[PDB]
Image (spheres, coloured by chain):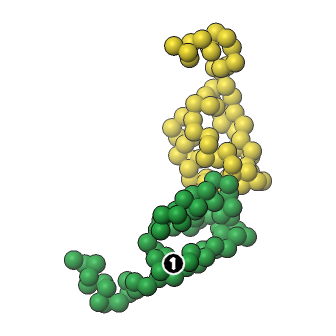
Chain colours: A green, B yellow
Amino acid sequence: RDKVNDIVDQVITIGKHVKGYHYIIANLGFTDGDLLKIQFGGAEVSGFQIVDYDDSLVSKFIER
Amino acid sequence: RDKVNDIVDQVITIGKHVKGYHYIIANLGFTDGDLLKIQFGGAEVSGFQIVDYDDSLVSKFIER
């Protein structure tokens, strides 16, 4: 989750986060990192999420 | 110098700082603001500088 943010930051700096690029975060924590930065860039970003925040079970956990 | 950084930040977020765009900072402090952000974006940025840091007079002032 750390080495990813470093890369993502560099990607935005050099401007390789615009339309045409496609990144895949190879970890079980896609929403664990900050995506607001490469969110409006244009480049498509995909990943994997193991903690479904749509489950009433998980939703209840977060509530507390 | 402040309202400029706000715009520059927004510009990078929406990704309108890549090659093809051309910005002109209409103030006497071009190097007064942070440019490292829209520096590698690709978009050309121009402006105006009144404090020439190449003058031995100014260079001596900065030394102190």
Q: Is residue A59 left or right of residue B23?
A: left
Q: In this view, does A27 lie to the left or right of A57?
A: right
Whether residue B16 is visible to the viewer of this picture, yes or no, is no
Q: Which of the chains bears the disc numbered 1?
A: A
Whether residue B57 is visible to the viewer of this picture, yes or no, is yes
Amino acid type indicated by mark 1: Asn
Q: In this view, does B33 lie above or below A16?
A: above
Residue drawn where x is 57% and y is 47% of the image:
B7
Q: Quadrant of the C terminus of chain A?
A: bottom left
Residue drawn where x is 31% and y is 90% of the image:
A56
Q: In this view, does A3 lie to the left or right of B40?
A: left
Residue furthest to the left in view is: A64
Q: Where is residue A9 in the image (x, y as percent from the top left)?
A: 57, 57
Q: Is residue A61 above or below residue A17?
A: below
Q: Between B23 and B31, which is closer to the camera in this rendering?
A: B31
Q: Between A53 and A9, which is closer to the camera in this rendering?
A: A9
Q: In this view, does B26 lie above or below A17?
A: above
Quarter of the figure with residue A10: bottom right
Residue at mark 1? A27
Q: Position of residue A28 (x, y in %)?
A: 47, 80
